[PDB]
Length: 12
Length: 12
Length: 177
Length: 177
Ligand SMILES: [Zn+2]
Ligand SMILES: [Zn+2]
Image 1 (spheres, rainbow over the protein chains, first blue to last red):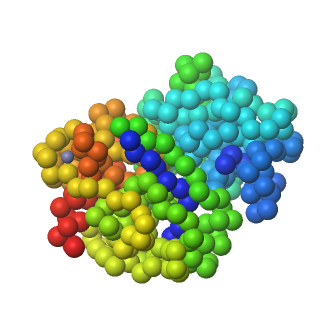
Image 2: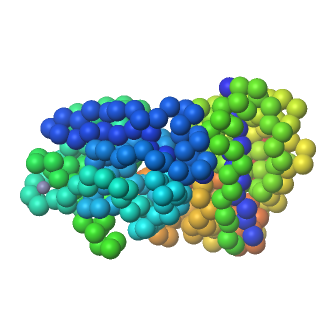
Image 3: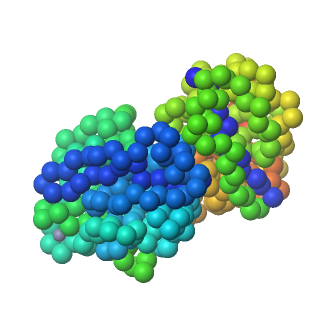
């Protein structure tokens, strides 16, 4: 099974 | 997205 | 000293109970097997507070009877967080013993000997694979009589062999309050 | 130089999206929180390519807008792999400005300070416990201007505490491009 993006991390 | 208790370890 | 696990929720349960944050399940025992969308770790109630490791919990709320329980104490720099214990919640008592003889309890109820090697360090009498301790951060480091001396953080390992543990002492937990 | 987490999916989401390999989800950010069925970590999008640790990823595919993507770069020894970034995904711009003052973004958006202590090392200012870093491999280390310098590869731990880190120099990501 694949690797999945479950979230993000917004920089500034 | 909350932390859910899915079980426990009974001490003795 | 022996412990035994008990599963209280399946897939559908964690997912719905995690969405809403509404867990009308009655809490029992002193250590809770908790999970998020990614990992699955452990939690220990010591003197009224459901404690756990911050890497696992982040800053998430615990699923509670009244709804989402925003967490109370938070020492991120010690990788620690805890929530105010839910109704019932059988807490543990701090050390008293001085005893350097600890035991680590895993997410499968493994009472495994550790020797108080420092303020937070601790030796494992017989090394095991690091897969053995997977999903146990948040667990307890007890004393001979069963008191909560520390909340287990991670194994100290080299070459896939884990021979030591790194925990937060019950005493710095209290210092947090 | 702040950063905040954001979940885009729950377990049911990782599960169905890892099975079908298809991800209709909009890519936004720079650092992505990614997961397999046995661990979770981060991925930093640099120069139009998604970089992450081979230790977390392995040879696995990345769920994409049109189906699963094959790694286009893989270096098992330098523990780094990459998939062409799916069209419409933000990407960090490299550093090379000599700054020794680096900041790494963890899985919870904690911008923790590190001093470059070598070519792929960086002294950790506030020696956090190692457990603290767990699940943050794959994430970036930026130079004061917010440009990329490498990918947090692992932790240089001294029996408990992590007083420094190992990362893939952005230069070793380019010799492989
Ligand atoms: Zn005691
Ligand atoms: Zn720079």
